[PDB]
Length: 160
Length: 57
Image (cartoon, rainbow over all chains, first blue to last red; front, side):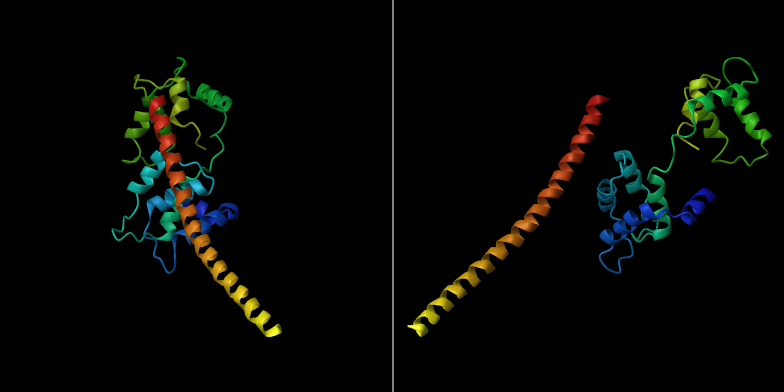
């Protein structure tokens, strides 16, 4: 979304040095970015970042959307920066508890994924295929018919 | 005496030239070998992390 565009605008130069080092290491001259996911993972490990093997697998399976290997440095760079950790623990657990206290209009020690749906509906925001289903699926991730407090934590932990 | 000494000195100089060239060859060969070694090391490291994860699970 627009957050990725903003992150592109706020290009952090400290990590930009390492990302352009990756640009140089990969591109051996007029290379149109064939996307060597092996080279991608080797760069990710080399540059000090800690990519999970599943993250590198996703990188392998979410590249070469052109079909010719040549992937625009824009989308590839966005994928690289987002796969890189850019977050501060996603708020505080005390904030989470206080806000869940706010959300417990049912006053039953938790909230409901239906209650969650209605509360976000009160926001007057667009709900789509990206929205709606997985929202309630992962809010009550354990699928108790209601969103427990720890379920509310696990739904959006580490996210700002 | 001086001319004979000149011939022998050039002899020794040329011998050291050739030896140094051979050594440079061996140096570059060991250099590419060392790079290959580092890559093998990193591959083994990744495999190790992976198998550790599996065993924990």
